[PDB]
Image (cartoon, rainbow, N blue to C red; front, side, top):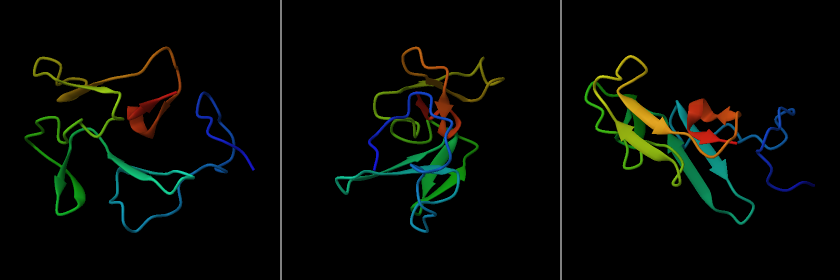
Amino acid sequence: MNMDSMDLLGIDPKHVCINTRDIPANAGCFRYDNGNEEWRCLLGYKKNNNTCIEDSNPTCGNNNGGCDPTAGCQTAENRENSKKIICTCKEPTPNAYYDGVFCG
């Protein structure tokens, strides 16, 4: 009874993803109305046997770091304080969802 709107919601999980057994832990599951399904692993997590594990050698951990397709994955060493992987948040959107995997 509603459409896509993630730009500052804060509402009850009416548009939340279902408890999935297909998507591994520490990953975001997005199921679209058209039937499309996206799964975004978190930063620092590597793809191991269709599962997301925290990897000691995360070369962005995922092709795009697990970040949204339009988010930028940046790898640094001197910034390991914030993490080994620094993902580029999206346009001015102070609402970071999925641990920063998606902004706004």
